[PDB]
């Protein structure tokens, strides 16, 4: 499932990782200890996206980039991780480009095949309560129970 008529150029730029739901208890545990700073979406050489995430981990600013390679429908991508020995489908399911994006990721190959994650991205680091409600509803409709939905800690550091 992808955002209809997806316009990759409008999806570019600065976003904030406001929320997460996943069926990985491990990932939820780790993510709740990270304080999110800012994320940047930039066009990649292969026609996909480079996603750069900046966050505070144990009082240290860290930034990590991920390559999202194009995968069929516009707005759908694949992420290859030799560390997880797996490939993941990453899709922009719903976005208005200028305020929010709801992403859904799932394993497509390898041991990580059963992995599932929904992500809320916002153009402000402090999104409206109605957007948080939208994300909660989206997560539940994707099969995530309430207690697997995480609104992530945020930081002013690392900007």
Image (cartoon, rainbow, N blue to C red):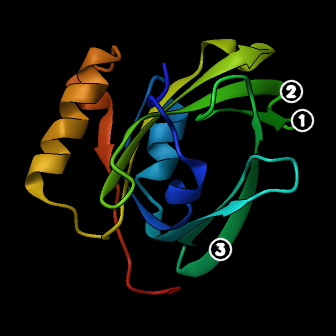
Check residue 29 in the rendering and tell me which mark sits there, or answer none.
none
Decide if residue 54 is on the left or right side of residue 127: right
Marks 2 and 3, Cα distance to the nearest angstrom?
23 Å
Q: Earlier in the sequence, mark 1 or mark 3?
A: 3
List x then y, in percent, for residue 12: 56, 62
Count of all numbered marks drawn on residues in the image: 3
118 vs 17: above or below: above
Between residues 27 and 107, which one lies in front from this camera angle? 107
- Element type where label 3 sits in the image: strand
List x then y, in percent, for residue 42: 67, 64
Q: Which residue is mark 1?
A: 82
- Is label 1 in contact with label 2 (beta carbons under 8 Å)? yes
Q: Earlier in the sequence, mark 2 or mark 3?
A: 3
- Is label 2 in contact with label 3 (beta carbons under 8 Å)? no
Marks 1 and 2, Cα distance to the nearest angstrom?
4 Å
For the point 27% across and 16% down, which residue is it?
141
List x then y, in percent, for residue 30: 52, 48
Between residues 142 and 158, which one lies in front from this camera angle? 142
Decide if residue 129 is on the left or right side of residue 80: left
Decide if residue 45 is on the left or right side of residue 1: right
Q: Which residue is mark 2?
A: 85
Marks 1 and 3, Cα distance to the nearest angstrom?
21 Å
For the point 49% across and 26% down, which residue is it?
2
Decide if residue 32 is on the left or right side of residue 133: right
- Element type where label 2 sits in the image: loop
Check residue 62 in the rendering and tell me which mark sits there, or answer none.
3
């Amino acid at each position: 499932s992808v955002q209809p008529n997806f316009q990759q150029d409008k999806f570019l730029g600065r976003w904030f990782s406001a929320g997460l739901a996943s069926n990985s208890s491990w990932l939820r545990e780790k993510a709740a200890a990270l304080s999110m700073a800012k994320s940047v979406v930039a066009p990649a050489t292969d026609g996909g996206l480079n996603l750069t995430s900046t966050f505070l981990r144990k009082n240290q600013c860290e930034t990590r980039t991920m390559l999202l390679q194009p995968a069929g429908s516009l707005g759908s991508y694949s992420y290859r991780s030799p560390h997880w020995g797996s490939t993941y489908s990453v899709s922009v399911v719903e976005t208005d480009y200028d305020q929010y994006a709801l992403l859904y990721s799932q394993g497509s190959k390898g041991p990580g095949e059963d992995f599932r994650m929904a992500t809320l991205y916002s153009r402000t680091q402090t999104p409206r309560a109605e957007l948080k409600e939208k994300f909660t509803a989206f997560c539940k409709a994707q099969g995530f129970t309430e207690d697997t939905i995480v609104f992530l800690p945020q930081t002013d550091k690392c900007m």
